[PDB]
Length: 28
Image (cartoon, rainbow, N blue to C red; front, side):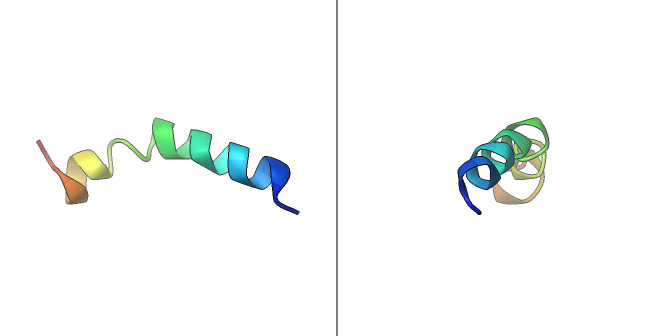
């Protein structure tokens, strides 16, 4: 489905999805 599968991944995108932007997309 989609209901948790959107919620769960948006949370993974904080815990590690910040450091990868602090690596490739912005890298400050």
